[PDB]
Amino acid sequence: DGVPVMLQTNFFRLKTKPEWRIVHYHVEFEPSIENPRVRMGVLSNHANLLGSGYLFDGLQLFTTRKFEQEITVLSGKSKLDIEYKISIKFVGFISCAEPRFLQVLNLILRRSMKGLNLELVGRNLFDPRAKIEIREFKMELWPGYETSIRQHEKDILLGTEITHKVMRTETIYDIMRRCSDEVRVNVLDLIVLTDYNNRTYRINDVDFGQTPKSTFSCKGRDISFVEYYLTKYNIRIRDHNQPLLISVVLIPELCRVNFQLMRAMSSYTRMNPKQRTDRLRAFNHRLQNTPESVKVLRDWNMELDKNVTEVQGRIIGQQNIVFHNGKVPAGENADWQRHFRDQRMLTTPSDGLDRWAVIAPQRNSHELRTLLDSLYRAASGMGLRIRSPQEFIIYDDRTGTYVRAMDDCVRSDPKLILCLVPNDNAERYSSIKKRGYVDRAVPTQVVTLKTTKNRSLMSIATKIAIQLNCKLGYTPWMIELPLSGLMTIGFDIAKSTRDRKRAYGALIASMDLQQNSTYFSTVTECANTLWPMIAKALRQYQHEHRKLPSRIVFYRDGVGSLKQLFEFEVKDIIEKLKTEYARVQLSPPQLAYIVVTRSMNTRFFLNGQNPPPGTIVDDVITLPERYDFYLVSQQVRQGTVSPTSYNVLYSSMGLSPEKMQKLTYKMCHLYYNWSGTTRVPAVCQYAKKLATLVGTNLHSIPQNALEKKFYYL
RNA sequence: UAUU
Ligand SMILES: [Hg+2]
Ligand SMILES: [Hg+2]
Ligand SMILES: [Hg+2]
Ligand SMILES: [Hg+2]
Ligand SMILES: [Hg+2]
Ligand SMILES: [Hg+2]
Ligand SMILES: [Zn+2]
Ligand SMILES: [Zn+2]
Ligand SMILES: [Zn+2]
Ligand SMILES: [Zn+2]
Ligand SMILES: [Zn+2]
Ligand SMILES: [Zn+2]
Ligand SMILES: [Zn+2]
Ligand SMILES: [Zn+2]
């Protein structure tokens, strides 16, 4: 297996009495009461059990004290001094396996979090007082804490994580003032979010005949909107002339209406492990000093441990990266970029770069020649025979000029087309990719002008040569794979920039890497559309190997909703694998279905630092019902590691869990755009890359001639 | 769009 270690976490133990159980009763009153809240008060009258925290819904009762039998209390109610007889009938104990166990624990912990007086939303606690406003980006970022609870045979654990909820400063009242019928045309059909209650509404009309001074009727009381929002949310309405949004009746003053913004926010969110540990200990000490939360915690006779729990784990040994003539170890820092310097790629076309073209404008011939010299040198050092491409010098840097050059050049049937661009323009890049992959079938390479002027142009040209070798459909390196007839599938999905109502699903499939070591890639728009792609992959596999694969490892990017995706995806997959292998009158293959999730909620560290690549936590902090584990595969220079969560829904592989984990760590070594281990298995990162390319730039399905090439890299 |  690997080298075992002990790792710091972000969980604290909830210690209770050694013999500590939860008692559930059903409660009823001799004088019947049509209102449950009155019953709650009537039971609250009993102080013998009041000091102990108890959960009463008007019928179900959860408490700690176990009574002698079915027990009955009696007293006089506050209203009319009516003699009431409460019949508290014993139901039983909540088993450690019942989900009501964790539901009761969640309600208790939420009651405790209430003492901190933080806005509670789902499993998150926010501090709106501590909002970070940004008028530069017109957005407010609220810090907060994400919470989770885990059950183990040894105890009960409670974990926290830093979280940031972002929202837009722009309000619908501001949009209406910018327009000032046209306001109604601009506002109707939009979705707004109330800043006092995490609810969104579709505005269907705007009533100009009503104001915040108008009144509505609740369940019994009549009240104005100003009074309602001052008494229910302590929110003051300053503008009295504004109209009302009718969806419910909302106030516009109180209604609120990516990849570079992600960079800015990451600059504001990247955190050293020590800083995250400090903020976590601060939150713990805050909850510990608050007497309101401590009262709730102590009433149930359970104590937070101000000390962090640590887990047993193991670090996978370094894996061997194979090239033509030899193989190298990955290293303690799982990066091998230093190694292809004076090393040859695994699979190289004997033809080499026998026919390709280069399109560039007349102004940038000098930088183009520099780039081409670097490419020749680097690709020759890699084993890639590159010859002189076809010169395609255009005059203007416009998009139509590039498109026309491509269409005039394709007539010579080139293996590849490299295009030198002036700047970082998504428009011309998307148009180039669309003309290359969708309308025609030519793998292309784009180089930003700033790249040519880079001082370290030689290592850049080496990485570009690796990318080009992949674009041709050849293999730069390979892992040691002790399995026969294995097909690894990755699959992911992406939203579209042109239309948010469509999504693209990309599927990547290996072809018995110990022999063929190539990949097959399909995309389709969102009638389950994934099985056609799986069938295409199996057909290509049997057309290349004269046989179907014996084992299949399916990596799924998603996620709880496990039950839904388990049922639908896995059941249909198994039935249709039965069917497809029955077409060949064969038995269905060994199948492993794993859901890959980047769990930013659960973290763990080694000696207070980021764990090294290959670290694994199996079945301690993981979910009890699931057969799953955590893996750290990609080391991070800066920031905090987000471990990957691999959840094996179905497994008929006949492989030990350690073997499955080692195979997954191996498959994490095969993303050719990155000279090291990636955060996810390689096929999954390929699927994400292809789906993002289709949904962001291509907006259409690429031609089927590129099925065996890494054109999307 | 060398890479994310
Ligand atoms: Hg249990
Ligand atoms: Hg307008
Ligand atoms: Hg009311
Ligand atoms: Hg050409
Ligand atoms: Hg899909
Ligand atoms: Hg993925
Ligand atoms: Zn019950
Ligand atoms: Zn050779
Ligand atoms: Zn050739
Ligand atoms: Zn120069
Ligand atoms: Zn995904
Ligand atoms: Zn255990
Ligand atoms: Zn488009
Ligand atoms: Zn690329």
Image (cartoon, rainbow, N blue to C red):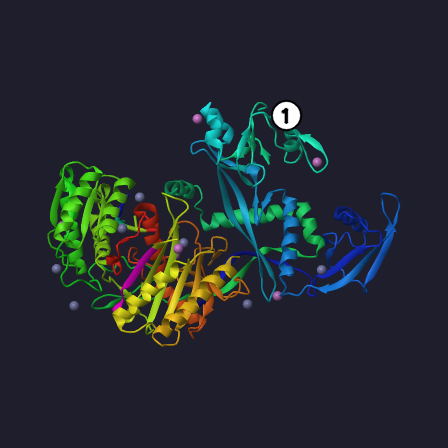
- Would residue A22 be counted in the magenta stretch? no
| Displayed quadrant of residue A558 | bottom left
The residue under the point 66% across, 45% down is: A115
Residues drawn in magenta? A515-523
**Residue at the spot of label 1:** A213
Disc 1 residue type (three-letter): Lys
Front residue (pair A7, A700)? A700
User: How far from the left and from the top, in percent, is residue A56?
Assistant: 73, 53
In this image, A50 relative to A581: left or right? Answer: right
Tell which subunit mark 1 falls on: A
Front residue (pair A14, A504)? A504
In this image, A675 relative to A107: left or right? Answer: left
| Displayed quadrant of residue A453 | top left
In this image, A263 relative to A16: left or right? Answer: left
For the N terminus of chain A, which image quadrant?
bottom left
Indicate yes or no: mark 1 CB to ligand 3 under 8 Å.
no
User: How far from the left and from the top, in percent, is residue A165?
Assistant: 50, 42
Q: Where A674 sits versus A593, above or below?
A: above
